[PDB]
Structure formats: C-alpha cells, structure tokens
Image: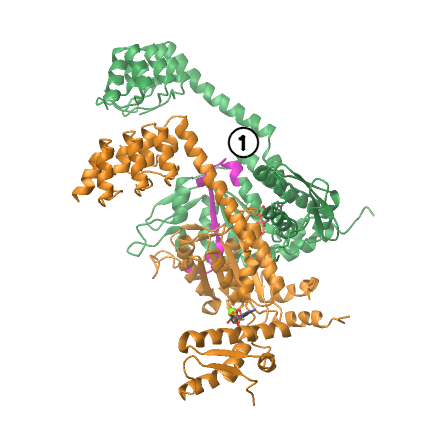
Chain colours: A orange, B green
Amino acid sequence: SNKDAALLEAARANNMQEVSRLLSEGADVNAKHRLGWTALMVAAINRNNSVVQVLLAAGADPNLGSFKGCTALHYAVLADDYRTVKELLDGGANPLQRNEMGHTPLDYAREGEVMKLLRTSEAKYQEKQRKREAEERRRFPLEQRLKEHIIGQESAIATVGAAIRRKENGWYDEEHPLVFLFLGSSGIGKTELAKQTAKYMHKDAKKGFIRLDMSEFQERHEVAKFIGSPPGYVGHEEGGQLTKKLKQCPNAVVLFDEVDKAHPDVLTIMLQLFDEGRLTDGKGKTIDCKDAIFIMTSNVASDEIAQHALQLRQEALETISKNFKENVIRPILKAHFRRDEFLGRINEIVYFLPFCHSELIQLVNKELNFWAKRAKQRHNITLLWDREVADVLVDGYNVHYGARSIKHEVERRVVNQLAAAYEQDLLPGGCTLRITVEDS
Amino acid sequence: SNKDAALLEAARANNMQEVSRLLSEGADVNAKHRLGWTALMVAAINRNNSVVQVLLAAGADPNLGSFKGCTALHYAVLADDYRTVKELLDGGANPLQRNEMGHTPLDYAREGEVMKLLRTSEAKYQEKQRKREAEERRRFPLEQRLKEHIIGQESAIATVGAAIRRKENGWYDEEHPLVFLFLGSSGIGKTELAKQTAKYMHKDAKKGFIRLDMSEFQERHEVAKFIGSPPGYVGHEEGGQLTKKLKQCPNAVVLFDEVDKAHPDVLTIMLQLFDEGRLTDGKGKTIDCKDAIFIMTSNVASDEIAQHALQLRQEALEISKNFKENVIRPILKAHFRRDEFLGRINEIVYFLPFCHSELIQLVNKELNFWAKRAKQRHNITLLWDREVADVLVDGYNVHYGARSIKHEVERRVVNQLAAAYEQDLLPGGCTLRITVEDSDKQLLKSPELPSPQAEK
Ligand SMILES: Nc1ncnc2c1ncn2[C@@H]1O[C@H](COP(=O)(O)OP(=O)(O)OP(O)(O)=S)[C@@H](O)[C@H]1O
Ligand SMILES: Nc1ncnc2c1ncn2[C@@H]1O[C@H](COP(=O)(O)OP(=O)(O)OP(O)(O)=S)[C@@H](O)[C@H]1O
Ligand SMILES: [Mg+2]
Ligand SMILES: [Mg+2]
C-alpha cells in the first residue's frame, strides 16, 4: 500500500527517479490517491511529460475515471500541455473520454496543439476502424460464414447477405427496422439461418439474439407477454419482457419462430415494431429499436413453394427461379395473416426451396463428419466411408422433414451400430472403422 | 462565490470598472445576492443605467425572479430611472412581469417615460408577434409545407389545412377540441400526414407530439394505461400516462394510430376527451386539453374507399360523394360500435390510392432521397434516366402503397450501390448514372461499373 502512495507523491512532484523506482518494484502504475487522482493523472495535471511517458511505458491507463472523474487525458488537457496529451493518446488514451461532469479532453483546453492532437487521434482511429472492418468483410463475407453451416438455399443466403451488407455499409434508411419473412417446408434451415445471422451480428453477445416461439402466443391475450400488464394488474411492475430484452440490446436480432402459430391479433402488435421499431410497455416507457433486425419463420405456403421449386426440376435440362408467381402466393399469406398492412411492412420475403440430390448428399456427409469427429474426440475412434454409404443414406430421405429426416436416417442406420459395438467393447481405442456399405 | 459577490457589490456601488472586470473574469451576471437581488437587479435599483447596459450586454436576464422576487425591470421602475427601464426592455424585459408580491413594472412606476417604455414594449411584442405569424403563414402555408412531404392526397391536404388555418386564426370554438379520423388503404401517408402536422404545429418540441399505438389496447382492461390504476392498487402513485403527457403540453397533437386495433370499450374513454378535452386520472386530477388536436388513423373501410377510386377509371370526358360517406358509415358503426363516438369527430379525411403520375413522383422522391444521402455521405453524384422511374413503378403493389415502392427501390438499386461501395468501385466525388435494362445497371460517369461478386 505504501508503494502506491509513494508513486503518487513522486508523480505529483515530477520525481522521475522515484517514479521509476516505484514502478520497477511492482507499484501499481494506476495507483489511486485518497483525493481521487492517480500517479499518471497528477503527472498530467502538473505538466510532468516525462513522468507521464514513463508511467505509460510502465502500463499506465489514461482512460480511468472540481475535477472529480477526470482521467489522465482530462488533466493533461486541463494543464493545456500538448506534449502530455500526445503521449497519453499514443498510450491509448481516448480523446473523447468523459468525467463525472461530462467534460472531455476536447473541451478543457483552448484551440491549439491539444485540440489538433485529439482530433487527429479520433479521425485516424475512425478511419482505420472503417477500413479494417470493410477489408475484413470483403475477405470473409457473411455468405461464406453461412455456407459453412447452411447447405443449399443459395437464393435465400444471397438475399439475406445482400440486405445485411446494405445495412452495414450505411446504405439503409435508419427510420425503419429491417424485417424478413422466411418461408419454406419444415426442416430446411430457416431458423438455422436466423441463428447463424444472429451469431454473425452478435457473435459475442447472447443478449444480441432475442428468440420468441409463437406457439407460446396462440391466443389473443398473449400480447400481454410482449408489453406486460397495465397499471393496477398483476405483473405490472415487471413490465414487458420483449421490451426489456430490446432495451438491453436495441440492435439485437429478433426471431419470431413459427409466427404462423400466433393468434392473428398477436401480429397486430408487430405493426409499430416493423414500421418504426417503436414499442411501449405497460409502464408507458417507449423502446426504440429502429436498427434491429426482425426475422419471421413459417411454412404457410410450404406445399405451393415446393410445387414451384419443381419448376426448376420441371426443366427440360437441355437453378434460379424468377418466382413472379409470388403474386399468387400473396393470397395465401393474406388468408393466414389477415391484414395487408402487416405484409406491407416486410422488407423481404425469403423462400427456402427443398433440397436437391447433391444437397442431400452434402447433408449426409456433414452428419457423418460430425459423428466421426465426435467419435474421435470422445473415444478416439477413426470413422470412414465411401459414396455407397452417402447414396444409401440419402435413399432413405423423407421430404416432410428434410435435414431432420437425414439426421434421423443417419442416427438410426449407422449410429445405433456404433453404439451397440462400443457397448460390446468391439471398438478398441484408436481403431479405425470403414462403413463398407453396411446395409440390410 | 467570491467573484459573484464582488460583481454584485460593484453593480450596487455603480463601479463600472469592477463590474467589467468581474464579467470578463467569468463572474455570473445573474448571481443572486444574499439580499435576494442580482447584479442587474441592484444596478437597476441604484439608477446605474450604464451598469444595467453593460450587464445586459454580458447576458443578464431582466425577467429573472420589500423587493423580494422583483425582477430587474421591477428594480429599475422602483428606482424611478427611465433609462434603466428602457435598457432592460431592450434586452427582452417583460413590462408585465410580476414580483413575489405580484406588482408589475407598470404598477410601481410613476407616470412618465417608464409607462411609455413599458406600454411600447408590450404593444410592440403583441403586434409584431401577430403580424409576423400571419405573414409567415400566408407566405408559407401549411398546405405547401405538407406538399413537400406528401404526394397526392390533395383533398386530405386541403381539409386538414383549412381546419388548421381555421384554428390558428382564432375562428374556432375553444370549448371543443378538434378531432380528425384518417381513412384509406395502407401506406398512403396517413401517419405521415399526422407527423407532418404535428411538426408544423409544434416546430420541434417532442412533448408537442404524442403517439399512441392503439394496437396495444386490444383488451378493455388496458384502458388503465390512459388514466392509471385506482387508489390502493399497484402503480397508483403514477398517474395516467396520457394524462401526464397532456399536462406537459395542453395543446399537443395526439395521434391514436391504428385506432381500429383497439378494443371498442377502450374507445369509450375518448368520449369526453373528444367532446370537451376532459380526462381524470386515477388520482382524481382532471386534465384540460380543449385546444389539443386529435388525429386517428385506420384502414377500416379501405377496400370500399379503394373501390370508389374506380371513379378515376370512369373517364367521362371520353371526389368521394356524400352518399358514399353514407355507405362508409355503416362500416364505421359496425367497427366503432357507438354513434356518440363518431358524432364527436369533426372531420373524416379520405386518403385515396395513388394514380400513375403520383407513383412516378414517389419513385423520383425516393431516388432523390437516396441521391442526397449518397452525395452528403460520400460526395457521390447520382443520376437516373426518365425510364428508370418507369421500370421501378412496375414493382408497385396497390395493397401496400408507397412502402412497396420504397422496398422495390431499396432492393433493386441500393443493393447494387452498397455492393459497389464495399467493393471500393465508387471513388469519392465520382459521378454515377443509372441506365435502364430489364434490370438496372450503373455507369461510373460513362463506363459500366463491373458488378462485384460477393460469393467470390
Ligand atoms: N439447409 C440446411 N443445411 C444444413 N443444415 C440444415 C439445414 N437446414 C436445416 N438444417 C439443420 O436441420 C435442422 C433443422 O432445423 P431448422 O433449421 O430449424 O428447420 P426449420 O426449417 O427451420 O423449420 P421448422 O421449424 O421445422 S418449420 C437443424 O438441425 C439444422 O441444423
Ligand atoms: N404521399 C405519400 N403517401 C404514402 N406514403 C408516403 C407518401 N410520401 C412519403 N410516404 C412514405 O411512404 C410510407 C407510408 O407509410 P405510412 O405513413 O405509415 O402510411 P399509412 O397510412 O399510415 O399506412 P398504414 O395504415 O400504417 S398500413 C411512409 O414511410 C412515408 O414516409
Ligand atoms: Mg424451425
Ligand atoms: Mg400508419
């Protein structure tokens, strides 16, 4: 504890020797004084450029929070010393950091070298971040990330990626959220695509992905879950759940899984959300989510979508459907979703088509790779197969389930055999299996 | 503290040098002395005309609140100095401002130049306000302001403008608030017109415009949100949300958006609100909002209104009638159950589906918006041939209205723009012109811009 006080006193007195001795002895570089200032901070206010430099080289943090709450950069600007401001900025100081009073390094000092340094640091940071992010996106676009997991559905991936890129590059109106409606048969990756998109946007934030299941909303009064009860009713003080989640992460990705299962008057609450990204809870607080992304998944027109997809498979063949027939898909949606204004607010309608033979083979290969890696990681068993296995597994495909049919087929026909053999201790650790078309 | 006291003493002592030095240092000009007066106050009371002038030049407020609570104009009047009163009035002092005891500068003053200055200031304020407001309204009418943002809907613009202008010029009954109901198909500017009207009435004040998404009132019990819970119930200490909002701005513009999505027993709360502008919160406090403007929006009769736009198809040479409004009524009563609710609305405004020229105008407006955004953000100049709008309008969907055009333009132009921008094929200051095929191509001032490949 004495080391921190000694370092603070040395920094206040501009004692280079004492500051260096304390730092080399393990003294807290960001030591805090009882008055609320640190060694780097009091060095900054006292125009101790050398002390500030040595403290920064020792690991001083200039962004740590009357001048109460003013950081090291704030005090450097207060002294109107440009050398200290430049050194702190080179050390990672934020030129726009704020104190308890809200003052910033860009306000304390008069126009001059300090302002120039702060502005240049801010501009260079912003430009570097912009260029780096753009280059990263170019190098590894969203489409490749989705293709890592999603198989087929090229049109849907292209549409979603185009919309997302248009949003990220700033070429989007901020007055209206972006809304998607995923349509297609069951078990073809709609909610999977939504999950992948949410992960891409908010990879390191669970709060960034808000999931709803509209099976849990199959009656009119279920709207009270979204915004909570009005004043004087049970649960009022709680407030809306969806409103809470949106307030936590305004730019999150909201997924209304199986929206078709909602009562139609539950969708009415979505009008303001989809138009202006505005929603009011039971307490009257209004949530602004203009930059959020809304995804709705349903299979309302599944049969018609499959029939259309046959168009590609109806070709004389001597892949991409124009799908102007959406004019006759609209009546189905209107019949289910009874309000035209609801559909009008949807930016894009994404159609997922049934898998082709090659896509089915790819799915089977994906499943067998997953199982092989699981076996290697768990029991250290190598697992291998040929075309005959993929084709035999595909032959058991069911249209009504898609990827789920493939999963069940692989599990039943192959995984059961691996489990039975393992339980019989016929699989020594490190051994290799070929599935030599093990059938019938 | 020390600087404020020094400035106050200098103002009291008529010390020009001290007052100037303290003002230059940064002493608060409106600092309050322990006796209740400020620097300007005591400069006025001591007949320090020059000190009053210099304090006003420094930013002194003459209208700031036995001379307890007296304002600088009050002190100048009490000093019997006409110069101080004149200078304070020139600084915006109110001749009718009241002190703690309720005496105005026109009261304490002795007959003379003080009366002249105060009365001249008051009359000038009133007449200048009236004349300037009238001149601005005539020069730039609300109807011309709306036309900048709303395409078509001439009959709605004309009705709303006529009612608004009627209210502003005082030719309205103050007992009953003005109520509008907006009817028509989806995405044809109802809420847009409401927003523009609110912005016009209250230039920027957020409290001047009140939103209410009636879609959140699908059950009777939700009406409690208007007025709050009764005594003894959770949330009672908070009053009615709408009551609070209206109290903060009695003459606000209230928008009950999607009123047809409310439970019809919830609309019952609006009977007194629309008839007399009275609403009593859960705590028994009544809100007076007789001068507010209420706007409702719905698409209740929208098939029947859009079907009556077959009058555009009648081509007699080769707009809604009273008798149509008596076919649109049965539909209104079937939805909004009560004749006493409908009989409270001042005007029913009908918004019609766009004709082909209005679609072209909408497409041009959207393209102009995007061009302005591009030019401002990246200095990119954007141009389009006349045929671009013709191609784009084909994406129009009568069921969705303008937002269909919005989405079409976005999807099939802005996507290419963003793809090119990310590809860095749009150098700053470059000129980009859209050309017309069955699809849309972009030329970078002459050569065709090569479409990037996201899939690589
Ligand atoms: N196109 C796909 N490519 C790879 N895996 C997929 C694909 N689609 C689905 N899956 C996987 O198969 C499962 C199906 O999940 P979903 O994606 O959620 O199905 P769903 O289409 O979304 O439709 P429902 O809710 O049954 S209607 C998931 O386990 C996915 O991981
Ligand atoms: N003349 C116009 N008519 C309709 N929309 C316009 C017009 N000019 C601009 N717009 C824009 O097109 C969109 C139309 O949406 P809204 O203003 O909400 O119309 P609406 O009458 O309220 O349709 P509903 O009942 O909510 S489905 C708005 O975002 C407007 O800004
Ligand atoms: Mg699903
Ligand atoms: Mg609307």
Magenta-highlighted residues: B198-221
**Magenta region includes residue B93:** no
Name the outermost residue toward the bottom. Answer: A440
Q: For the N terminus of chain B, give its image quadrant.
A: top left
Q: Return the residue nearer the eye: A68 or B94.
A: A68
Q: Return the residue nearer the eye: B96 or A414.
A: A414
Does any atom of ligand 2 lie closer than 8 Å to the CB of label 1? no
Q: Position of residue A320 (x, y in %)?
A: 68, 64
Q: Position of residue B369 (x, y in %)?
A: 61, 41
Q: Chain of mark 1?
A: B
Q: For the C terminus of chain B, give its image quadrant.
A: bottom right
**Magenta region includes residue B203:** yes
Q: Could you tell me if residue A292 is visible in this image?
A: yes
Q: Is residue A282 left or right of residue A40?
A: right
Please identify the quarter of the rendering in which residue B138 is found: top right
In the rendered image, the vertical position of residue A383 relative to residue B134, given as above or below = below
In the rendered image, which residue does mark 1 sit on?
Answer: B169
Residue drawn at x 53%, y 72% is A366
Name the outermost residue toward the left. Answer: A2
Residue drawn at x 60%, y 32% is B141
In the rendered image, the vertical position of residue A301 relative to residue B370, given as above or below = below
Q: Position of residue A387 (x, y in %)?
A: 60, 79
Q: Could you tell me if residue B252 is visible in this image?
A: no
Q: Is residue B395 left or right of residue A423?
A: right
In the rendered image, the vertical position of residue A278 relative to residue B432, given as above or below = below
Q: Amino acid at mark 1?
A: Asn
Q: Few, some or many C-alpha atoms within 10 Å of disc 1 (few <14, some 14-19, many ≥20)? A: few
Q: Position of residue A151 (x, y in %)?
A: 58, 68
Q: Return the residue nearer the eye: A259 or A197.
A: A197
